[PDB]
Amino acid sequence: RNAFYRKLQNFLYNVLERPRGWAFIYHAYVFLLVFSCLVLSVFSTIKEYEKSSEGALYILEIVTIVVFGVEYFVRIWAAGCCCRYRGWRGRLKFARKPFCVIDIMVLIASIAVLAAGSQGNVFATSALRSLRFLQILRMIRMDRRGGTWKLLGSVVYAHSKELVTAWYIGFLCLILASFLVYLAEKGENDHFDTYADALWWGLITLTTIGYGDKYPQTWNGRLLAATFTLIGVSFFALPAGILGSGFALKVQEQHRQKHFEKRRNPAAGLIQSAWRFYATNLSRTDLHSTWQYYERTVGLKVSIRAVCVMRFLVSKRKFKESLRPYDVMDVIEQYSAGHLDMLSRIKSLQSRVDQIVGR
Amino acid sequence: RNAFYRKLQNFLYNVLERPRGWAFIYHAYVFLLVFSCLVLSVFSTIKEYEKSSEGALYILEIVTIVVFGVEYFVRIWAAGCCCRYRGWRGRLKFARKPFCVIDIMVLIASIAVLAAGSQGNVFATSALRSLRFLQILRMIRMDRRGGTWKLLGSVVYAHSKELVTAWYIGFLCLILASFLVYLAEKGENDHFDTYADALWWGLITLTTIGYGDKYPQTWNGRLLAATFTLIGVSFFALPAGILGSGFALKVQEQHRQKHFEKRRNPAAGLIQSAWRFYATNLSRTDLHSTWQYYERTVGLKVSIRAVCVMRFLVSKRKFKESLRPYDVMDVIEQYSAGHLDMLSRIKSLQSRVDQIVGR
Amino acid sequence: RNAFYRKLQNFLYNVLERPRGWAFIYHAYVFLLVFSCLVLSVFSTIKEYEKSSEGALYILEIVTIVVFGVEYFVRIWAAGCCCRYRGWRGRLKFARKPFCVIDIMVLIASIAVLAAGSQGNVFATSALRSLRFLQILRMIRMDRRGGTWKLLGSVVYAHSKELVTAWYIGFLCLILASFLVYLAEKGENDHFDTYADALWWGLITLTTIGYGDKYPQTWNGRLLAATFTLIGVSFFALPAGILGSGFALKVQEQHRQKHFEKRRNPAAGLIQSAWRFYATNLSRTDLHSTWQYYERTVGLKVSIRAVCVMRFLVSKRKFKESLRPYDVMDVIEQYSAGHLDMLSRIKSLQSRVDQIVGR
Amino acid sequence: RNAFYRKLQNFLYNVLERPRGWAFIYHAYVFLLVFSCLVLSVFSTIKEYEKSSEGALYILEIVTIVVFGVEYFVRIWAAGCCCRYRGWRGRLKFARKPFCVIDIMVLIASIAVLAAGSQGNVFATSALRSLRFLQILRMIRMDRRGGTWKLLGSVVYAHSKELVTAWYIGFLCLILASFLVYLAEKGENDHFDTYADALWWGLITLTTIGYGDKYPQTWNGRLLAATFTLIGVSFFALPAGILGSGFALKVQEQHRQKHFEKRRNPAAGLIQSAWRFYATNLSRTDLHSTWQYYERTVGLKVSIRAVCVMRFLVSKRKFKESLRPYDVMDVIEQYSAGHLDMLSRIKSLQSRVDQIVGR
Amino acid sequence: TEEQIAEFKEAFSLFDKDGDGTITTKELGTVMRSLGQNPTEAELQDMINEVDADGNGTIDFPEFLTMMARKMKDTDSEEEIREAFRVFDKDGNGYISAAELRHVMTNLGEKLTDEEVDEMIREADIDGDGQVNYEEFVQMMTA
Amino acid sequence: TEEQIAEFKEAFSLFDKDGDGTITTKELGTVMRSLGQNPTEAELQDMINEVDADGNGTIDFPEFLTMMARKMKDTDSEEEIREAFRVFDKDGNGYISAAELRHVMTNLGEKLTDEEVDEMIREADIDGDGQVNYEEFVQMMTA
Amino acid sequence: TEEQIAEFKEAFSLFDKDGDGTITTKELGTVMRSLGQNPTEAELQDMINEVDADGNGTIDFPEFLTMMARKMKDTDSEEEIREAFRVFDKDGNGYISAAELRHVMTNLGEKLTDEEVDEMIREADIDGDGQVNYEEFVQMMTA
Amino acid sequence: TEEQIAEFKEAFSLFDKDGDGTITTKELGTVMRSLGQNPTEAELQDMINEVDADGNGTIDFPEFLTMMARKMKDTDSEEEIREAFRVFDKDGNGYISAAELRHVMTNLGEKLTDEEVDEMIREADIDGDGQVNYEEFVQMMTA
Ligand SMILES: C#CCn1nc(NC(=O)C(CCC)CCC)c2cccc(OC(F)F)c21
């Protein structure tokens, strides 16, 4: 069943590499399993629940090594589906991907720690640390693309000036308020023994964590703390609000722009122009016969080649400016072109009717 | 008074099912009553205020069973107003609605617990649990449509990628900061006895709850806690800001789009086309006489039917693309069509004036 | 100096009633003074700082009664400037304004409490409560228009559905998490003695206040608290973010719309139409001579009156739809009208050129 | 190497004064160094880590004085590159800049405190305070332009009304809730001894700091605290959300507007008009020969001068309205002009075709 | 009075061209084109909407008479005119310089002649100072 | 039945002008211009799209017949017609006054004559009260 | 000087066509059409606005003379010209290559001839290096 | 080779009309109008921009020859063609059905004939299955 085999392999590749829709379910399950393991590892640290947590953790470690090995082999097969990695050499080339090699390294580490535990020589602390680190490593691997980091960095850089303003003003407010409260309390309050303690109090207050170990206990200390916290809490909360609003606005703008679509025209122009520019052959029976057709519509050889490259070049630029269309640029440029065109045609109407009057 | 009876029944149905405006007041009152009951139930748990709270709770339980029964009967009558549930069978069909059956089940449970309390055999704990659960059930019933859940899910899915980025980065920051502070403190601080305690501290800090039971007490622990919290608090606060900004932007976009309106044209076209397509009868005295009129304006039978269905089909599509008009799609498509039309007519002007010059 | 007196009176009226710009400075000072008094009143409650705070409070009370009396008299004079309150009867009419009568009542109460303190019979508690309440009353009076309340209510109603979703989901999460943690801890933890205590803990946690008196101390309690808080904190923080984003979007939309301006055309039309409709007199030497002029441009009397009222009526509607212009409505309607007009004129071009060909 | 020297001097000036891109790296490093020093200063306050922190602080102080001196001299050289400060007098004029004089004062203070420490007479407290204040002074100097303060003030003023609404409503809620909880608890709870304590509790609660020293312990106190905090926390969190959303919206609007660009046309017109208006000379061999050319295209002298100034004036205005183009103003005005122009030309078409019919 | 009804009928017939008992958009357009000002079809349709209550697309005699019986005092017209004046009130106190009206009121929208604006001044400006107070003037018109 | 197929072929030939076995946009345009209503090329292209499944740019006999075999009951047309009626349902209960249809249904979009709207009324309004209930009417049409 | 006033009056009469003592939009339009460049009515209205202070819709002799008495030094023109130069300053230091002006200054807006731009260069570029420094040049023009 | 340079000069003269040693926008427009396709001035200006490096507004012989010496392999053209193919890759694996190209590649933009698209198929589709793999094809063209 060649068709069935290809269809199944493509389906598995889509699920394991490009989970557009319901495929995410599977990934979630895997994450859950991994996450569950992590939680068990935490329970393994506690000495009270050592036995049951250790047993469940070993069972889940066996299950997860099995699942990860099966997934890795199936992912090798799926990458085999992709033309970029067709054949044994292509699959090996795919397996050199940094995330794939990281995953296989984690798998080998897990099987190795299990085997060492079977041996018994390996200390329990070593195995626990190893398994915890492998679990977090697969957690990181879940991204597999760096999409979250890239998005966060993009939004942070977009609001770099505003974030820096928030950080700078909040830092100045923290320093000033901590110093003033330190002066107010100093010896009166045991909490504010040293300026380092005052800075710790200020950081824990303006962030609104408010542990309660440190807090002013004098009338002037409390007065200054009130006046300064009323603004410092907002300053320290600013970055979260700025980033959240930026994320929401970016989501809105994307849901508009990527929902525009209506593209691939410059890409089609590129395909045509590359085809014609490759066709500029040495008078062989290939498309250069179509080039003789093209020149028929009209030494001359060079001009033909020239024009082909020209379309190629121009097409390139179009796609380059059409890769990420901007609504404001599109609308402004189209309005300018259209209105200028209509005005020019109207003036042509005036000239033509004037000559008609002359006629 | 047929007119008066119909008007009153419609008014009650609107109040109890489609509370557009002032009708909400009534619902609020009901909620308040239910909410009040809930609060009393809480006071019933405390052993100090058992007597007074129990007496007031019994009085309010009688009042609320009475009110809910009256409301249920009046709601059955109101649904009777609706044509979909006209007649005894229609009203019974209405009563099968999941929320209606849930409400009647809650009513029976409340009357049953009251009767059991009258009997005295039922234990007080059973009655208290029953009444608390029925109260929360009616609280959930207040929605009656799942609107809140649907809206929250829609906004969450819209920002699924941003929310996942926030969760992932915050989780990584929590794990890293908790582990580093655990290493810094470990044995020096009694609070951070085990890594589970460190994780609890990290969760309570980055969320800014800051209970105060756990907090670093070492110079390196406090330094790392400061550096990591300064960013972790923002990361954990991100989701609230993202969701709030998304909600506000959605409200703005809705207050624009639903404020557009200017629709029902495709719906009217659909009505006309369905009427004409039904009219394609077997040469009877019905609209098919109007079909003879339509064909008069021009074997042929099929074409008539064809064209009728055709309008139907196109009408359908129009309404489908006019159900939820998008400002950007509307504006872009209308601009393209209008400018292209004007340009084509201008070129027609050029051709016609050229031939006039020829004439 | 009639001109100087009128100019000064207008300047004081603008400062005291319509503080557009730098005038706000003065108001701020007054607020500061009032606020200072309030703070002193707080220090008066403390028994340790009774003497100095009482002395400063009495001095500031004398100062503030003097300032408020001077301001009230000058405000009477300023309202006298306004034509609406010209003359003694006009000033008395202005003085019936609820905020003015509230201010004079507060002034009388302050002078009365000062006189009673001079007498000595009045108990200190009575005077302290009186002065605190008068201070808060003037603080409320600072608004003088209800602008803050109106703006907050407008933004809240705009996002009524989203806010209700946030409240409902957060309430359900609070109830569920509190009950689950109560079950987990119950007797193990002294904090969660009763479900009321669990509800208090849940409210103080999800709001992120985190006092620290209540907190889970069991493995299952802490696990459930983590899972539920991770979402409850965001749900409870939602309303602040929603309102803030709504306020920012409203500010943006206002800074666009009110910055449009370009109006008063329908208002001018209203002025003209009202002038002409009043002019429809009983054939007297007033504008009805201009009505004879108007009818000259053409029993007939009624038509004249008709048309005048007609302009009036239409003018009204225009101003009514031009009071709060909407950018989207303006742009969409102007685009529709303009493109339809151009298309119709283009078809007129086609018809005229066709007949020219015929000619 | 004149070219090499000029290029290097310009590169250093750009890095030290206009760090557009990668140059920021250097600044960051400097900040880090300064920041590191600050942290060491904090460790110097603690008596336990006095020795090591003092040694590292002295080493870093020597390093930072060296770096700041080198940077100041190189910045003098760089400002020398700028034409505004060419020559010795120009460099001296640049050195009078307030930030430059502040920096040199800080440098002198640092070298002076180091020399005094070498002498040993200066008390350790004096040196520590001096170095801490100099460190914060350079931290402030990092801005060098007041950009953060200006941006924050702009956004705050933009949302002045909304922020004032938030502050006012939150203040009223704080006062009311604190007073009600004070009445509820008063003598029952030791925490709420006096109304000042109640106000402190209310401030620490509504801000969500929640130290835990103060918290209600009575049924009515807790009930009122719940009802009032549920709204007060949101009111106090509002300003952060409002400012964050405003910052994000401002970033979006800027990333649109400043990304428009397509300007310098009015600036070019201004340059031309200034050139021509200067050219209106006393009939000398300068551009006034070009003025004879200009008048050739046509006592008359004045008109020439008139028209030149006129372009100047009009050019000025254009640039003034083109300095900060607004998308809404640009689009609305261009639409009005274009549509009115097309309509007028269409009516010209109607008139011309009518006369052609007459012809 | 019967004389008013006779005037109403006479002018309604005058506006009527075909004689259908109702005034159409074209009738108003042509009669006010004879009046010198050429309208737009939107304005005529607006009149048709404002007079007619049954949506007949024209102006019938009953609605004509009912609109005739409605004088300014019975129009609830105070708020609209007050707001229109206020939008033109730069100072906001309520006084407007007659020169301001002459510059603007006769330069915007339905521009009026010098006689009409000066009559406005002498009507509203009872004091004859130039500081016209719109509130009292409009209130006494609506009396 | 064979008679239906003969009718189909006869009218398909009638629409056909050049005789290529398919109906193009121009054929539909001209035939329905003879019908009195002049379309727009967008409408004809929409018909070409909705009939044709192979994207030939015209209407062929097989797709014509397949569309013919699809009656209203086999169209999944209940939701669209119900929604269209609902958008016109001001009260939202499901009853619409026949006068409302006469005022609107014959005044918007493809306006219909008095006979057609009255036939709609007597069809849907079985009770003959004027409170037409669209749900039952559309359901029984789709039967 | 009286000679300057005589020149002013002579040219004001020259611009004047009907002889009303004021220069209208059409007068400026026709005189500068004779000058070769055809304006737009917006530009002529802009001149009417910027000269006239009483809003007469034209240019009168007193405002003409007052604008004449205002030389560059008494115009507060430093900021505008500095900003205009800065917007064209790519490097931002204050030096612009004369080749840059030749490429741009004569290719945008009111494009000037080679003679005018070269005279600009030899005027501002005292050093004769091509790195024109706009600040000193504009300051000395405004002197 | 000298033959290539002779060809270059011969065709450059052919395009040249006035004989100024450079090819202007009008020359390209007229020569490719003879070619059957009528351009827009924007396209000719785009060509002028892409060839010319000194901004002369035309195409000179040196830039012509330099552009001639640049073959596909020395164009850094892999990314653009790969991205263009990817945007058309619905599945995203890298395989496209030749029928998909025939339906789309010859129906959008610069539509090509059946011969050209079939030659594309037989060129890229070495396996002759219809699942053209654009990556290898474009890479080997760029070889
Ligand atoms: C979610 C959540 C927490 N939250 N937040 C609230 N805040 C507001 O409503 C407005 C007050 C004005 C109506 C805040 C804006 C000023 C609120 C009110 C009632 C109950 C709540 O919890 C319950 F629903 F779980 C509330």
Image: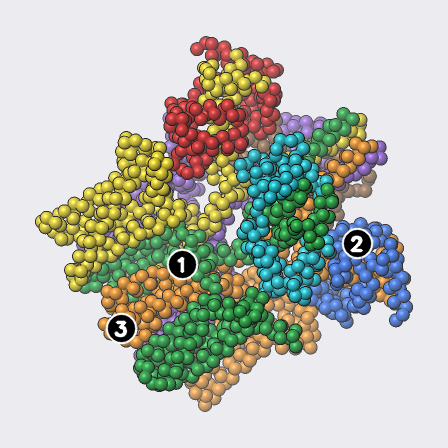
Chain colours: A yellow, B green, C orange, D purple, E blue, F cyan, G brown, H red
Q: Residue at x 58, y 19 (%)?
A: A297
Instruction: Give the secondary structure at mark 3.
Output: loop
Chain ID, mark 3: C
Answer left or right for H6 relative to A231.
Answer: right
At horizontal 52% and vertical 66% (from top left) the residue drawn is C153
Are discs 2 and 3 located on one and the same chain? no
Can residue G126 be seen here? no
Alpha carbon separation for disc pair 1 and 2: 59 Å
Q: Is mark 3 within 8 Å of ligand 1?
A: no
Apparent side of residue B341 relative to residue A26 in the rendered image (left or right)? right
Q: Disc 1: which chain?
A: B
Q: Circle 1: is it few (<14), some (14-19), or many (20+) Cα within 10 Å? A: many
Residue at 40%, 65% in the rendered image: C170
Indicate the position of residue B179 as horizontal and vertical percent values: 23, 54
Give the CA separation, mark 2 to mark 3: 82 Å
The disc at residue B240 is 1
Image position, residue C21 (x, y; %): 56, 60
Quadrant of the image containing the C terminus of chain C: top right
Picture layout, residue D18 above or below residue B175 = above
Residue B92 lies, in percent from the top left, at 51, 70
Q: Are marks 3 and 1 in contact (CB under 8 Å)?
A: no
Q: Which residue is mark 2?
A: E25
Both marks 1 and 2 on one chain: no
Q: Which residue is the site of mark 3? A: C186
Task: Tell me the distance, in whole angstroms, between the alpha carbons under discs 3 and 1.
Answer: 31 Å
The percent coordinates of residue B309 (x first, y second) are 61, 47
Residue type, numbered disc 3:
Lys
Amino acid type, mark 2: Thr
Residue with the most extreme front position = F2
